[PDB]
Length: 263
Image 1 (cartoon, rainbow, N blue to C red):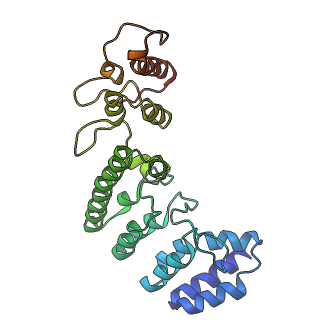
Image 2 (image 1 turned 180 degrees about the vertical axis):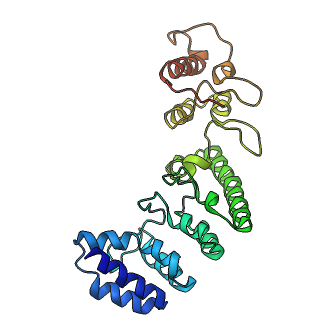
């Protein structure tokens, strides 16, 4: 039954009519609880990238990817769905030299161009056409710079909601290094908040991956940026309580870190 569904879907995709595809799915890809139906639908974007016109690929993505929209399909297609080879639609598009599809996918809100297939390759490495590879490299570099800016905006305005959205992004897990030097300031975030003496932000950063063993551009560890104070107990040391708290936090984090960032 799965082979039948695959052949049926590919036939509709090759014909290139989205309205026809929509009707086909609505009437023949039922019920929603059929395993084969679900499995083939999950690979629809892969198959579309292989045989369908740009217009169809665009309609598929705009109709069934965004989780904020309810549709008849009743399935939110994953733009980063991995097939049995670990390939995503972007991997397929890059290998098949469909530059326009590659660019379109890279412009989508939920795209993750860092997914590795079973051979440990990213989509950009699938390119035989290096002009397409160059375009992917430039688009990634632009995104990296804009995201570094987004992160700076969020932490400098102390917007935890925004920070949550930035660090929870699958793509940012690899394109935004909380322990790396910012491309514009050259500074490392934990260090900056230690100097700012914002302990709550420091705690938040540590819980989200910030490493107390990381040295910034000046070769300084976060703990070395704490005010040079003697006392280890806040009792009767009210005027340096924040500094003591900060020192204690970083000392504890240094013990708890477990995995030191290696560069």
